[PDB]
Amino acid sequence: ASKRALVILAKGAEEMETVIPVDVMRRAGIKVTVAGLAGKDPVQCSRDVVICPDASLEDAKKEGPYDVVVLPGGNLGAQNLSESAAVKEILKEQENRKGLIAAICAGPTALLAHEIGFGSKVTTHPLAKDKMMNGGHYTYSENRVEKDGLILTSRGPGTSFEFALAIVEALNGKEVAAQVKAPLVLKD
Amino acid sequence: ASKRALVILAKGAEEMETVIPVDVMRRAGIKVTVAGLAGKDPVQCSRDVVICPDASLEDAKKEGPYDVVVLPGGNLGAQNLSESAAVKEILKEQENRKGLIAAICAGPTALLAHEIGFGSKVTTHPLAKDKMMNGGHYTYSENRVEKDGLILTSRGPGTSFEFALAIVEALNGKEVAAQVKAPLVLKD
């Protein structure tokens, strides 16, 4: 009866956009797997924070399905996610089974690379808008958090808490999200 | 001409309160050393995020002095910081040379354990107030960020961005903090 989350961690990922959702989701009782794109080895994030993943993406792929797949941002991290065939397979499968897909900042540009969720309203970091909108396959939003169907997007490191709590609300409901939120000392 | 920051990382530390200041400070051009209390080995944080430190605290101690010493929160992380003699030596030295000391959430309780900054106005996480105020050696504040002399404190994971930007402003000034802040997409 426990929900499961997959966080895909690639070199150059924004470590704040990786750790906040993982932390907040585990506070909500969600079983989170931080899967290294390139294997089990430690991952050097965009600001040189080094994180040890829980598993390789190859191994975590076999232990699905997941209720949410989370794509952190970071320009170079998002590029690595966009070039990976394993990520394409995971996202297409998740879209087919109508599971939740969550991406923040530059992360949503991986959805375009893999042709995921065309026609959805999405947001990105302001600096990633032009890349996300190449071809006009999505409709752009400036909301700090945007959810259209099974596609949940957010804008930047400073929206990471709202992004993470939106996932919790989608998976575990509004009451759990509010309980998890109070001890964090968030402003609004 | 480069400012230097020391972040002391112990088991049970709150990984969000560790990664946000490190990331934000490196965005500000500050040279940050994430020093493992127990050595160079990876550190399991409070929500099971595993971080590889840049150096052992023993090694980082020799490469001082630092313009700021940063103590993350996390109840068990703060207890480990409070029991460490090496931390006592670093903090007392930092206080004598009138360097900045920054602690967030449960982190400020390590200041009480090591008799640092008595008489200062400080804040903590609401759940750590009673422990911080044992003996009445400080004056308590409910501000999200509190700075009294060389003691800078903050309340919780949700104040981590404001806590980190206050450090940048103290070290590099108000203009740099504002430049670093804009791309984060913070609300206020």
Image (cartoon, coloured by chain):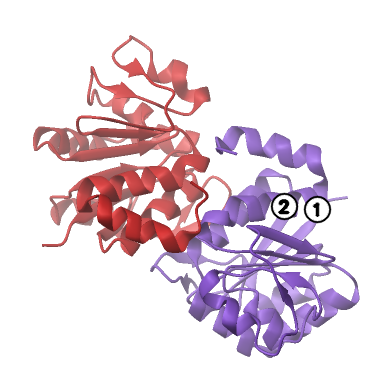
Chain colours: A red, B purple
Task: Find residue A122 and report its horizontal and vertical position in percent.
Answer: 34, 25
Q: Residue furthest right?
A: B97
Name which residue lies at 42% across and 50% down: A18
Mark 1, chain letter? Answer: B
Mark 2, chain letter? Answer: B
For the residues beneath circles 1 and 2, the answer to whether they share a chain is: yes
Q: Amino acid at mark 2?
A: Ala
- Up/down of A41 relative to A139, above or below: below
Q: How many marks?
A: 2
Q: Residue furthest top?
A: A135
Secondary structure at badge 2 equals helix
Instruction: Measure the alpha-carbon separation of dots 1 and 2.
Output: 6 Å
Q: Which residue occupies the foreground of this view, B136 or A39?
A: B136
Answer few, some or many: residues within 10 Å of disc 1's Cα (few below 14, many 20 plus, some between 14 and 19). Answer: some
Q: Which residue is mark 2?
A: B166
Q: Which residue is mark 1?
A: B170
Query: Badges 1 and 2: C-beta atoms under 8 Å apart?
Result: yes
Answer few, some or many: residues within 10 Å of disc 2's Cα (few below 14, many 20 plus, some between 14 and 19). Answer: many
Q: Amino acid at mark 1?
A: Ala
Task: Find residue A43 and report its horizontal and vertical position in percent.
Answer: 45, 54
Q: Quadrant of residue B125?
A: bottom right
**Is B12 positioned to the left or the right of A54 in the image?**
right
Residue B114 appears in the picture as rendered = yes
